[PDB]
Image (cartoon, rainbow, N blue to C red; front, side, top):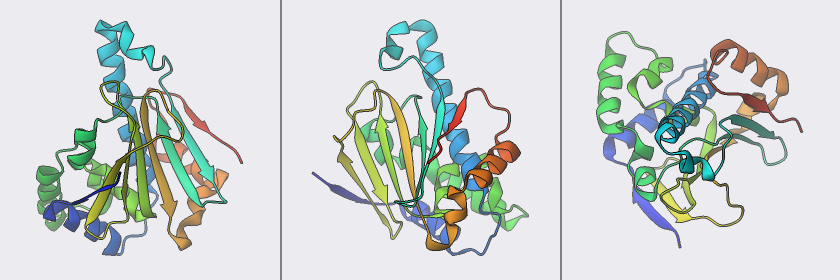
Length: 208
């Protein structure tokens, strides 16, 4: 069933900085996740060009943003490439060890925290708003996995069967108490218009 792993010391530190550095432009987290979703979708398009069969698991290439005010979660879903157990475990397929280092080198020399994603580690910006992140994923070459973390130094991976998802990645953000603004329809619309306005894939904003 559940496996628990430690974050590489460096990522544990990056996460820590995000959680513990005072920085109020928290909204950028949405841009960064949306920007991973876009890339993930880029990858599935790229392979499909040579191999139509890769989109047997779904033809549509899009992003859903799903607020749920009851559970207090913001879910970002794509039908992009997904991650294998191994990518999941390895820093969710980022070059996070090298990218973290640079980011901090770059932080000492005039970079703010919103530059995070220029270092390939935008994912962790989730922790600006989220107390706990669950990432469900399905890659064509593997089964469905759930990854989970509330920082603290550890993450867990387990396989996942409650609802198959064909192909893609579902980043579930359980918001901190004081961050429920990110569940308001007008706040999400404003953010998407302001930071992810022009992007290669449709974004549906679910209503409640």
